Image (cartoon, coloured by chain):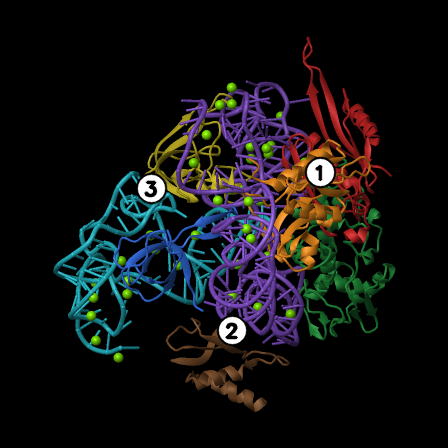
Chain colours: A orange, B brown, C red, D yellow, E blue, F green, G purple, H cyan
Amino acid sequence: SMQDPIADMLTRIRNGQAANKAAVTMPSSKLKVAIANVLKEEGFIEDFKVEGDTKPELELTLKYFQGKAVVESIQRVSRPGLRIYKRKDELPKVMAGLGIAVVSTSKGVMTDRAARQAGLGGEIICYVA
Amino acid sequence: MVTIRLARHGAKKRPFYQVVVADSRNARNGRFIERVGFFNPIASEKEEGTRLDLDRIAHWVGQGATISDRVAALIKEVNKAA
Amino acid sequence: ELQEKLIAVNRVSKTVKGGRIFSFTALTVVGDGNGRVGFGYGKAREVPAAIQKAMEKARRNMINVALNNGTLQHPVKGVHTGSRVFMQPASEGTGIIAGGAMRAVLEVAGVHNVLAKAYGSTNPINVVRATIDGLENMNSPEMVAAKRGKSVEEIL
Amino acid sequence: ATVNQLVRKPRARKVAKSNVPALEACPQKRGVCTRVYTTTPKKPNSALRKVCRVRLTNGFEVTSYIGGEGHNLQEHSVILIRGGRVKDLPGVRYHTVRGALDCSGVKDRKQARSKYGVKRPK
Amino acid sequence: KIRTLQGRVVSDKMEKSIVVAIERFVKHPIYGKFIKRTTKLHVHDENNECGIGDVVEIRECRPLSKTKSWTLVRVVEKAV
Amino acid sequence: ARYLGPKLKLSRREGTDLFLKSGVRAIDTKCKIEQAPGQHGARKPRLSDYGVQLREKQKVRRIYGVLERQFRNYYKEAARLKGNTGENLLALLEGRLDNVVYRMGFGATRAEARQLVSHKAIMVNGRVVNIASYQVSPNDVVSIREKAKKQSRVKAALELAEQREKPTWLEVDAGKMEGTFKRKPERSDLSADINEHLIVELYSK
RNA sequence: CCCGCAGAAGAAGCACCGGCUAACUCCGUGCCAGCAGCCGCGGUAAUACGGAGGGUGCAAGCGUUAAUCGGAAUUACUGGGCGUAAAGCGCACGCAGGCGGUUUGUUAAGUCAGAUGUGAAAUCCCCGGGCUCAACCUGGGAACUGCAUCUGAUACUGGCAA
RNA sequence: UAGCUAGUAGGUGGGGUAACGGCUCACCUAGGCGACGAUCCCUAGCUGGUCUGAGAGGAUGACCAGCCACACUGGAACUGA
Ligand SMILES: [Mg+2]
Ligand SMILES: [Mg+2]
Ligand SMILES: [Mg+2]
Ligand SMILES: [Mg+2]
Ligand SMILES: [Mg+2]
Ligand SMILES: [Mg+2]
Ligand SMILES: [Mg+2]
Ligand SMILES: [Mg+2]
Ligand SMILES: [Mg+2]
Ligand SMILES: [Mg+2]
Ligand SMILES: [Mg+2]
Ligand SMILES: [Mg+2]
Ligand SMILES: [Mg+2]
Ligand SMILES: [Mg+2]
Ligand SMILES: [Mg+2]
Ligand SMILES: [Mg+2]
Ligand SMILES: [Mg+2]
Ligand SMILES: [Mg+2]
Ligand SMILES: [Mg+2]
Ligand SMILES: [Mg+2]
Ligand SMILES: [Mg+2]
Ligand SMILES: [Mg+2]
Ligand SMILES: [Mg+2]
Ligand SMILES: [Mg+2]
Ligand SMILES: [Mg+2]
Ligand SMILES: [Mg+2]
Ligand SMILES: [Mg+2]
Ligand SMILES: [Mg+2]
Ligand SMILES: [Mg+2]
Ligand SMILES: [Mg+2]
Ligand SMILES: [Mg+2]
Ligand SMILES: [Mg+2]
Ligand SMILES: [Mg+2]
Ligand SMILES: [Mg+2]
Ligand SMILES: [Mg+2]
Ligand SMILES: [Mg+2]
């Protein structure tokens, strides 16, 4: 079954970028929408929309720069099999700060840099590069 | 009996004493309740060579701890110095 | 100004009807010491012809690497076939710490300070291919900011 | 491989087996020589290799190779044996220390004297 | 405001006593997985009021028997 | 605990002048400098990567007259210290008392400076210091002792230091035969034919 | 510890030199004697055996043996695999266990933040001080990645309700 | 090594201890522990630490300091804070 819906979204992004698709769609959820906001604010995707009321569909427009995918690697870190939680002083930085790690803190999901600046730790959703 | 005495540390021929409060039954370098200073009998000039936390000494003496004669001499010398 | 190093020479055989025919291979790496490094293979009957064929091939087939003051921008992993290579930046004065095949390519490319490790097969031909591939797949703050549509400090 | 599987059965290192069990984690062992003889080597090499059967102080009975050119050893000679096996000689896993209790330094050696128990010539 | 534990009743057969499970959620030292761990305690309940399956709050006190050193404070959700 | 063998042998093996003699004579008129020692010196060596690292380490050690155990301790200290490990190792070597007295010129060679230090002829901050590996500090003043001031070797050594380049970091008054170690030398103040990075990697192995 | 006397005067060895691995020639021997950590050497030109000359590496030490970790990502949590190289149960049902689509509320167990207590001293680390230097000794700090209690946060996970 | 356990699990009362307590006894209930490894067998003093490792770890517990145990072997009490 679909035990990990967040990983499903990342995989759709990864496979769609590999297949040079203009946009990708997936069933929505507030956690997915909250991650998509972080991706857009960090410039890894162009834009996103939510469509429908009874079965909301989330749609992300992917992003290319030199006919190349902006998201080079995007991997799930905390997974249902093994949850990962970091304290404020252990928040990872990916690609020496060039990328981002999405961290869910008590104040909503944000990037590792923002959470570090806000002095919080939390669950590590994924690494984006 | 709680007592305040010197535990001999340092190297051969260069004694360095740790002023410690401890139960009288334990070994000289054995388990101690608290460390309250140090004494250096070989210290050169411009080195203090003797530091005691007088407040802690007073606290423990008020609880009834005895004082070794050597550390009693140190207290008097320090109180004379300042 | 291009700097060139012979990494490995090997003697191969063909086993023709009359017997074994022996020929030699070379492995060479050339670089400008300032971010351009290429490798050539080179194969010939005699060792001098082999090393010469390799160097000429290496002068072309050369790529550019976004170096950072003689050091890597960020940790990178490179895998060719059975060799997996890990290289991460280090502080000035650390030296180039790496296996022999990686040592030559990093020296010639101009990476003065790197910590490196080779996992899997250490076959020189594939190790060099894997480290070059890893170095090319290493982006810089300006190009990542341009790609992400922001400024450098906004990325920091 | 799965973490769940590892929690139920942790990874279990293979225990290293020693190659000189008679020594029993000791640098050298003393023993008396039961029989001194010469045996032929394995297939690639051809020579007469001098070996001795030794009963060690711990009960173990082993065969120790005698290095160097020439030896004065016979039955009831007490010797010191150290680890190390002469590859092309099946069964032999130890070397007798020359210059030990009864093994004597090889006569007229000049290079590598320390290995063969030869005092420095005057 | 005292230290206390909450658990579930695994057995009520003994007279004036019960055994409770105080299962806790802890991370594994090596692999990092969070695993449930269960600790069984023999608990004292005067009035013999605790039935199996109840959730109970317990407190630690002086030894009352060879194996029993905890006493019941109150039953939580007595329904079974 | 010291190299008491022939000195120019080492320079020939390393292929360069190691300043093991006073300098009154051309080293090439003193030996076949461009040929390796021994029966097989004529052969040009095709030394490997381990070979080149080893040769650089030996060059530095033979320049300063230091044995390997002490040299390895210097590397550990340099690695522990903050900053560039290679430049720290050269700063530590320069700080040695024998090198310092040789630099201010109270000695024709580092061995000659070593004998002067060993025979209680050198004072630092007015205290006679007899240890060759003593580490000198900035603002320290190193002086020749009074009884040893009348040594003809010391006078001749000062004249020889004239021909060599004057070290920037240390200021010397020859009339008083005393010098002040003003500061730790930087890398640029030292010779540019030392490949310290090779030594750092050699201990990385 | 300081001063004086005499006189270079009383004071250098051990391993290695085929490749890995820094350092090569001659003579003896002739699948013998022997060497050997691994690959291998030796059958009349041996840089691999034995001696010599030369050289390299360490040095009041230098080699050998034993033992632990490393290299070994060769138990792989970090950090591996399973078509043919070792490796998918012959197949299925299924209890314990592991995992759980979406929305709201509540809870605050995991998680996170802060505070408090404790985490002996020594040791390791940082800045210093004292033995002529160093080893050694020593002042202050950091650390002791832990545990418990209290106070807050509600994203995520869990519980409860819909 | 898959079952182990009759003072065994709990309760009431008496005795006992500096002190709570199957610590002991009588009566009563029939329990208790175990697949989150009981029981059985082999090995072993434990820790701060030491060594190795980039780290995570691995090996280890000489010296120094804390705690335990033992004093030819087995048992027992006496005196005493
Ligand atoms: Mg391999
Ligand atoms: Mg085994
Ligand atoms: Mg020494
Ligand atoms: Mg060589
Ligand atoms: Mg040999
Ligand atoms: Mg010959
Ligand atoms: Mg050899
Ligand atoms: Mg030979
Ligand atoms: Mg070994
Ligand atoms: Mg390992
Ligand atoms: Mg494998
Ligand atoms: Mg097959
Ligand atoms: Mg198969
Ligand atoms: Mg099948
Ligand atoms: Mg099924
Ligand atoms: Mg769910
Ligand atoms: Mg569940
Ligand atoms: Mg909580
Ligand atoms: Mg401590
Ligand atoms: Mg000092
Ligand atoms: Mg200290
Ligand atoms: Mg919730
Ligand atoms: Mg919830
Ligand atoms: Mg009573
Ligand atoms: Mg009773
Ligand atoms: Mg009890
Ligand atoms: Mg025992
Ligand atoms: Mg024991
Ligand atoms: Mg490792
Ligand atoms: Mg242990
Ligand atoms: Mg002992
Ligand atoms: Mg006793
Ligand atoms: Mg006895
Ligand atoms: Mg007795
Ligand atoms: Mg009494
Ligand atoms: Mg009594």
Label 1 sits on a secondary structure element that is helix
Q: Residue beneath label 1, please? A: C102
Eye-nearest disc, 3 or 1: 1
- How many residues crowd around disc 3 within 10 Å: few (fewer than 14), some, or many (20 or more)? few
In front here: E1 or F93?
E1
Residue A117 horizontal/vertical position (percent): 69, 59
- Compared with G7, B49 (above or below) is below
**In this picture, residue E64 sits left or right of residue F123:** left
**Residue F130 seen in the current view:** no
**In this picture, residue G155 sits left or right of residue E78:** right
Q: Amino acid at mark 3?
A: Asn
Label 2 sits on a secondary structure element that is loop
Tell which subunit mark 2 falls on. B
User: Are discs 3 and 2 less than 8 Å apart at CB?
Assistant: no
Q: Amino acid at mark 1?
A: Met
How many numbered marks are there?
3
Q: Residue beneath label 3, please? A: D58
Eye-nearest disc, 1 or 2: 1
Q: Residue beneath label 2, please? A: B13
Q: Amino acid at mark 2?
A: Lys
- Compared with B18, D99 (above or below) is above
